[PDB]
Amino acid sequence: QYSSNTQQGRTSIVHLFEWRWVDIALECERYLAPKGFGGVQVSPPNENVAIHNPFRPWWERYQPVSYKLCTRSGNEDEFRNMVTRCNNVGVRIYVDAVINHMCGNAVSAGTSSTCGSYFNPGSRDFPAVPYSGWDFNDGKCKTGSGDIENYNDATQVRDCRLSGLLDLALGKDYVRSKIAEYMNHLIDIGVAGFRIDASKHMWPGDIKAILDKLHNLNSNWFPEGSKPFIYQEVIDLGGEPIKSSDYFGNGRVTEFKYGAKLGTVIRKWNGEKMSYLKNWGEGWGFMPSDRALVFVDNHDNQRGHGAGGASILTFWDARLYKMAVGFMLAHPYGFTRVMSSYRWPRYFENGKDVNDWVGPPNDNGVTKEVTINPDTTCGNDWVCEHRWRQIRNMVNFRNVVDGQPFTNWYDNGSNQVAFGRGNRGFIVFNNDDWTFSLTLQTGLPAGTYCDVISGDKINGNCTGIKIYVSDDGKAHFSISNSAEDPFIAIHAESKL
Ligand SMILES: [Ca+2]
Ligand SMILES: [Cl-]
Image 1: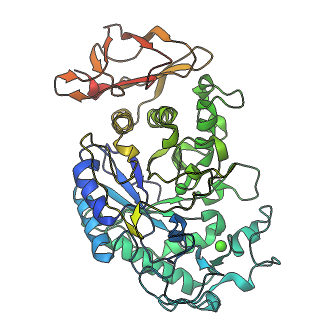
Image 2: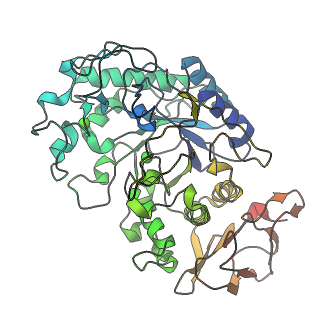
Image 3: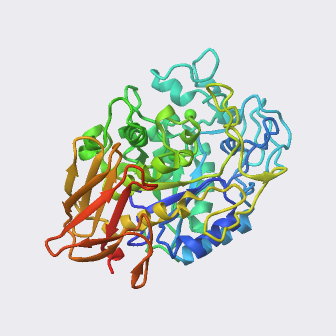
């Protein structure tokens, strides 16, 4: 469950947050495949509650109603079409599996679901599964509210309701079975793995019992006996009874400490500096690299939710964001996930963004299609960070240097750092308040290399900066602290 199942030479997955199945299919063929992306993390494909107040929030997708593949992203036919098309071009699909719970216990009974399924939270009635009151942890929880009240108690964290969401009795084989049913349907369609939502709220043992029941990957695209890639969402910033290491037997685990710290360093908070990154990874208290799923931001925390609070870098902080993503893609630690967002009318009613609930770009609830601009960016309020030249090019940088050691580290003891990846890549950063101008030892063979930050390599020439590496492998770098993109990156495949 630790291997991504991506093609050889494709080292990252992109989260296409709330995208429609039809758009993802197109994206796989017109961009992801040819630009070297390894896979896509999709939003929950199962039927959820349609919340009308506030109006169709993004988080309604984390409140399941059934396991029918019918959401704002599309129906089963479209989902199947998407997986097939992406797989045919070597781009994998990873499903966001919401299995800890069903909907809010105070939601109202009826058919206000994305597929019209009837459900009654008050009675714990989910006929479309089906689930009854005998399938929820109500009796198992021991809190006065039946909700999670204290994170120092491992048992309530897992047996009580997360903010009122009906907590499934994962201890029962029936429930584990229904879930496996759902997950197997997806595997047979062609999904390469899963993001297990709210793993912190489940017992490692229950998760295990579910994985036990899963099929191997679809033998049309995956060699016989392949296991689904598993990455568990466990928010662990330390000092809690529940530890991310508790989940290592099930697969990888989200390393939230990564983005929190990268965010603090780049924002130069708490007297942190880039030169401190010289021992980035385990050296900073992180989980083993072979179990980490890393990212700068996610859907929760780009909204000041998740974990990291105010330090998290996002598309809103574009210049610094590109730097952080760049550093992540160049550094050997973990399996990387790139975020792809949508713009929302962020509005601070002093302190808090009161619109952090707003769902994807829509017309009366119907998700808007992803349009492409002439400059290869996206319209209809889709941010498409994965299409930003600097990010897209760093995804390819990672592919090219995969497996190379961390070498030729340099720092000015402040915020000017550089490092190479064997003899296949070199990156330079200037996050100080003055120009960086120094001749560095790169570890790269002589020649003219296109900087992939300021431009591209287009057969025979560079459209941005050119770096000349001398036969002694030295190159001169000059980066103004005022540059749009205060970093340079060259690699074996950007060489003329
Ligand atoms: Ca639970
Ligand atoms: Cl996540």
